[PDB]
Image: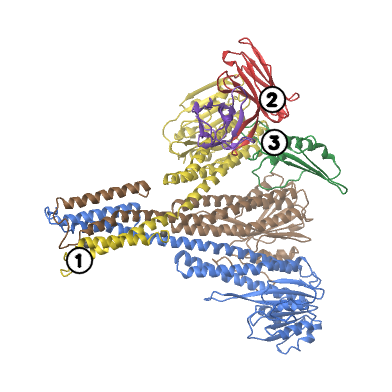
Chain colours: A yellow, B brown, C blue, D green, E red, F purple
Amino acid sequence: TLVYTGKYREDFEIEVMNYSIEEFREFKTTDVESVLPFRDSSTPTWINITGIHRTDVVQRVGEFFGIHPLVLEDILNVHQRPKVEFFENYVFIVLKMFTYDKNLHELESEQVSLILTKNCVLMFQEKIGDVFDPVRERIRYNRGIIRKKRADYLLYSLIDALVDDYFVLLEKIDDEIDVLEEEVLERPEKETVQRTHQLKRNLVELRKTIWPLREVLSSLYRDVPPLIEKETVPYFRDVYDHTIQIADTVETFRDIVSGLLDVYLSSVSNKTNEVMKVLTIIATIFMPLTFIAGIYGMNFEYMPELRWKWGYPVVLAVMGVIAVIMVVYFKKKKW
Amino acid sequence: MEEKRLSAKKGLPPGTLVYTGKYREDFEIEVMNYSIEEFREFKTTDVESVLPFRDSSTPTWINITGIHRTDVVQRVGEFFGIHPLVLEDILNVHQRPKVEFFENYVFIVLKMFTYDKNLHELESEQVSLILTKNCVLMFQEKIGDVFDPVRERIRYNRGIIRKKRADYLLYSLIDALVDDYFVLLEKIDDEIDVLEEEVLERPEKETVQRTHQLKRNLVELRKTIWPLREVLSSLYRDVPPLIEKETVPYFRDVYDHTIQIADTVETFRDIVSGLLDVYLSSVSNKTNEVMKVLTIIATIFMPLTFIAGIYGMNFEYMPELRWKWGYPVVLAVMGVIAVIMVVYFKKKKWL
Amino acid sequence: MEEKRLSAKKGLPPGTLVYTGKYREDFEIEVMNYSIEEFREFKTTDVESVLPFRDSSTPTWINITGIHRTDVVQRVGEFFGIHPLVLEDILNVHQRPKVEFFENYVFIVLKMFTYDKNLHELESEQVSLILTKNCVLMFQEKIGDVFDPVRERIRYNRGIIRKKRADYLLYSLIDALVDDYFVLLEKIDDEIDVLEEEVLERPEKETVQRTHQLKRNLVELRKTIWPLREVLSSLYRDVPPLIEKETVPYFRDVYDHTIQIADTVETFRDIVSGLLDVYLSSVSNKTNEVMKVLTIIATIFMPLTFIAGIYGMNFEYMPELRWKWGYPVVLAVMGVIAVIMVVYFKKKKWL
Amino acid sequence: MEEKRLSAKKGLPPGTLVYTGKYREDFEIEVMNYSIEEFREFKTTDVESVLPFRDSSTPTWINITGIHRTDVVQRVGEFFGIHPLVLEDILNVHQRPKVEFFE
Amino acid sequence: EVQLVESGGGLVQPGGSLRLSCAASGFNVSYYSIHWVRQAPGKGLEWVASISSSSGSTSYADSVKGRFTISADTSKNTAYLQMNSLRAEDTAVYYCARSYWYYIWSYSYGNAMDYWGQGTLVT
Amino acid sequence: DIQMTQSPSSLSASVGDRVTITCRASQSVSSAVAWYQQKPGKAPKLLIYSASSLYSGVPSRFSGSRSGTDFTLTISSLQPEDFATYYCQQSSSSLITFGQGTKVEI
Ligand SMILES: [Mg+2]
Ligand SMILES: [Mg+2]
């Protein structure tokens, strides 16, 4: 029980920001105990655990905050679609941050768990690197209204940063779509086909990850248990609409890339004709020549192979004439 | 015959009834009486509790599971004043979903689907709902259904399920069925995605078999879904006196959900129809690669084996019988022609 | 359907009624009078015996098996006040199922099919059912019908057929025909399953012919069955006076049966459309593996022919110069290149 | 389905209505006010001329060709009491056919 | 018919202030977005600020943030840009341009300014 | 901030020629690039929006193309009225950014 599933073993650090209307303190540490006392504090706190491959810390904080070990295993589980679970003590959501590489077109996903408990938010991540820097400066520099509100608005801000990163990823994918759409039409090779296959798989992954996100954000503003407070409904509504936008773009891109695949797949089944033509013309050309050469190659010791009128030039001339005749046999039916 | 889809060879007089499905194992009657004040669960294999609950003014939900005991079904039909023809419809598991309105009861037949992974086989089970007075009768075949959330809502005083009469109960059960359709459509979407990937990049015969089975499953769903649209439309528009209004808006949402399900099923059918052609062309492309390999080797080989057979014949008056490094000259020609042929292949991307 | 005038054709003189079908090998007449008290049956080919049963108080059924003789059909029609256009429609076999309503009688044209195993022919014959006063006239093309169960039901007094009027007899005949349709659809499902197993396992040449024949049969069934929905919908909704409103639920049930049959036909059409693409994929796979074999043979035996031709040359100054018994060395080099190429194919997994 | 209100789209000011098509060439307002006696055809470009026909007793047909000018659509909706979400649905083009019944 | 007129320009002392007024005719500033575009003498165009009067959401370039302030009055159909703490690089010609939005994909929108005024010189 | 560069900084051509001016965006702007024309001493005039669409009333000599993250404005056949400066907008973000402008002269 309580086993880590991902593939990250690089770094593990803990970060805490405690902000109020006037008070603010941000720090980083690597001891699980130091973040424990913040639970009973009335101030809105943000706790971040970058490395969850150390299961002991995860279990320790789970026991401290009085949460079910099943959701502990869900946090440790990494291959899972986003979901939302409303419990009386805490509300627990699962999201996925995406990263893209334009040099090598691949999509990397990281599972991130967010738990809201009264005046605290707990974030569990896979590796180091976040999309929450804008909200980090929002708390740090007091710009914006993040400090005035409670931890529900902090959950809203984290989800907003998530969907903003989704928008950036969609911009990168749109540029890739344009490049590939031009290249497939005007540069047909195998690398284009491999890139199109990779792009289709990446868009399928995006669809499978984003469609449950719509349901999560719908739940966070329709069911709205007392944890989120009635003052935060419109913001989650806005994030829900943003998720709708991201979806609709995802299906549009999927349709376009499927059309590209269909075009290339239609271009195939005519290379068979060309290659068959090449094979059959070279066979019809060169099998007769080999046939005659072998026939004159047999040593029966009684063949009229004497010089006479020079046999070798005559044989070569006749063979070349036969080859030219076989060539002329083609192109009559447009071969 | 049993494994085959249709086994409805009946003929027979039109006034007598008999069960048709493949399930003859379980039998349980679960009666749930409820109101604003308190609820009451009677679960038994006895037919005693089901009978008198029609007269009770409080709403009741009878859930009879197991139609292999046709005697209890016909007995409760006789006691409830239910026409024998719709009894035959209840026991007939091949009947498509539908609704019929009478002066005393409204009768509905629906199909619930369960889909299990690694065994690509949709399983359809018929559920019959008869709403009359202040009770709802639920005829079903196997143990296990999707109506757990409505049971939880009834027992735990959440939602409006207890504030209204049996019409809201029927609405809630139909809504639960539609949600089950949605989750099964999600399962089939996942299967379609993985099958599209496998068709594109792993062409095997097993892939074709899975594609055909998935096509059959989507055709089954397409057959079943449209009568559900018709039945929800009939409940939406007709407004029988048993439906006490202020629930027609509640049925409108279910009608919209059924429309969405129908559109999704049609798109899925389109995708699974295109899958076979995609597989065809991918296998043709692999064959084209085989053609590339064979044609390349043939065109870079057969011409110079003709060349090697040129001087292979022994003439009495043969040219270049004795020249310096004649065999090395032939080998150099062979290498040069091989190199230029490889150059052409690199030019044409064939190799 | 009015004006009391026949259609005008070139070949026929205007005033003649002509049989259209191809069966002229039979002629029979039967009369069955049924009631609560007893039942009378007689098979007299003489056409005079059916006349007195025109005005029988009890409902009676007159079956004319074989309408190839236009004399009997025209005389019966004139005797019963049948409009000449209705008589032509009875004689015109090549006509889709339909119902015409008149102030005196109700006219219905239907088809019943027969399926023969080991001989893929989905033939048909047209039957005409005319309900007038309290007697039902049914005309058939030839011998062979699905009305035997109704006949034995009348004989054995089982059911409630003898407790009602001719409208219920017409309902019983239509229900028997619809059950015949169910049986035909089941047999076609059997054929589809056998064909599917064959195509997924053994892709012979006859499989294409069987698939296309079954497709044509299914299209013919759809063309026949789609007007049957209009038939039964008219009989149910339009509520003509002769029905007398008692048989509304039975006619509605037969309408539901027709709708289910149409949906089943559409399902079978979808499956049949899938089978052809499955067959194309299977034959593509077969071609692919055969060309696997051809390539893996030609590729490995080309360079060996190279070494054979080069070293089997004819030159006085040629560098053979056997180095430490080098002929087995050349053979071992041949084995080495053969092993290299088969290893390459194994890595590419062609063989 | 719940309540309905204007969607919030990233990158736009709140409550901004945008035409989502590709045609931005034509604009006209053609009005046909007909009755049992005589008709009235009136093709124009000014948008204030057509607005008073909301209270006309005889049937009126107001055909606005060219919705790329969102200001005209917004003014017509504001005068006619059309809900802003309906205006957004009018301007939004990537939409399957639909019907909505309001009061 | 659509016209944009710029006024309020002129020479001013460094570190001072100047209010530029953009009067719009033929269209309602409430329904559209209004941008200020700055072109230095013999230099390329630069973006100053944008106002969406219906929503009130304003946007500023990072090079004039804080010093410049943009607002709009719907009653007069006017767009005001008041500039404080003016510096040496601000001497330029200011244009006022109305822009609409267009739809590329469901996630991305762009705007193109249709009608521009004659512009006013500020030193 | 999204920085766009544009080349060439000045292009010389005669009437009847084809002229292409290309913008490169540092970041990724989806397709919200706009091409404007400014004659000396007068306000700019919008020519192209959405990287491939023509503003109403603009002559079809100008055309626009987008390859991934760089855009091109191509004039098929010049005219004496097309000898002006051409500018380049990105509008994906709320902060519009211009190019430095290319003067097409004789
Ligand atoms: Mg030889
Ligand atoms: Mg082939």
Q: Classify residue E64 as left or right of residue C66.
A: left
Q: Is residue C185 above or below residue A84?
A: below
Q: Are marks 3 and 2 on the same chain?
A: no
Q: Give the residue type at disc 1.
A: Met
Q: Quadrant of the C terminus of chain C?
A: bottom left
Query: To which chain does the residue with label 3 belong?
Result: D
Between circles 3 and 2, the one closer to the viewer is 2
Query: To which chain does the residue with label 1 belong?
Result: A
The residue drawn where x is 72% and y is 34% is: D71
Which mark, by number, is residue D69? 3
Q: Is residue B266 above or below residue A65?
A: below
Q: Give the residue type at disc 3.
A: Arg
Secondary structure of residue under mark 2: strand
Q: Classify residue A94 as left or right of residue C236.
A: left
Q: CA distance from mark 3 to mark 2?
A: 18 Å
Q: Quadrant of residue E69?
A: top right
Q: Give the residue type at disc 2.
A: Leu
Q: Are marks 1 and 3 on the same chain?
A: no
Q: How many marks?
A: 3
Q: Are marks 1 and 3 in contact (CB under 8 Å)?
A: no
